[PDB]
Image (cartoon, rainbow, N blue to C red; front, side, top):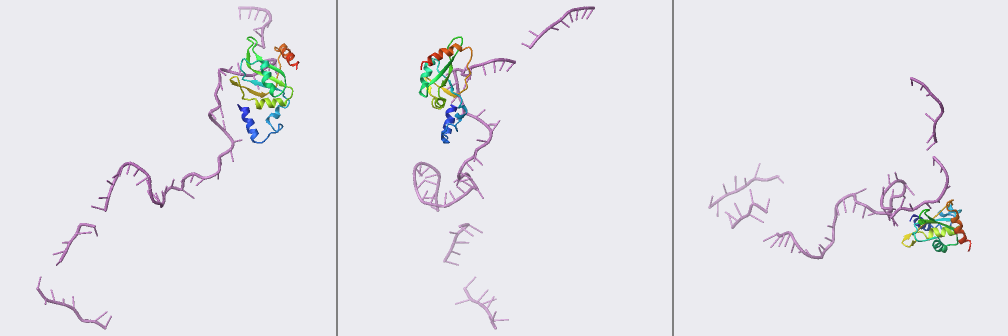
Length: 128
RNA sequence: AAAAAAAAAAAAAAAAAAACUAGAUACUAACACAUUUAAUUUUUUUUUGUUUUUUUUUUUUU
């Protein structure tokens, strides 16, 4: 896990400031990439693990257009962008149901074929 | 500086091991004695990182 190696070397250099961090590049990005998921975990199951580090306002699990089953990666946006640093360097390499997940910062591009999916997601997270 | 004589018993071709097993303690080799710090395989997983885009002949004749 390369992200977990560069946080150890950053922490030993005594950097500890977010603006001197390698995280600083992604200060405008509130989305995260989540990868190497187990196939049984779902959208409401992703919001449960990742709510430890903040309030997730959008979520997208990517799953095939034919068979409708999980490709094994998702996307999640937090209300506060500093929750992104939390999730990235504190939940990375965490074994969940056999496999260790990979979290990275990201720029998310929404698509047209998942449009009404985005309101089937939004009406859950508009409740809270 | 100096100026000999003479009266018939023995002879030898020259203190030590290999082993087992602890033990004395000299030495040898310009031996090696901050580190060497930007090109280059330990880095391994059941493939799985989400927008747009990268073309076609008019008629005819020997």
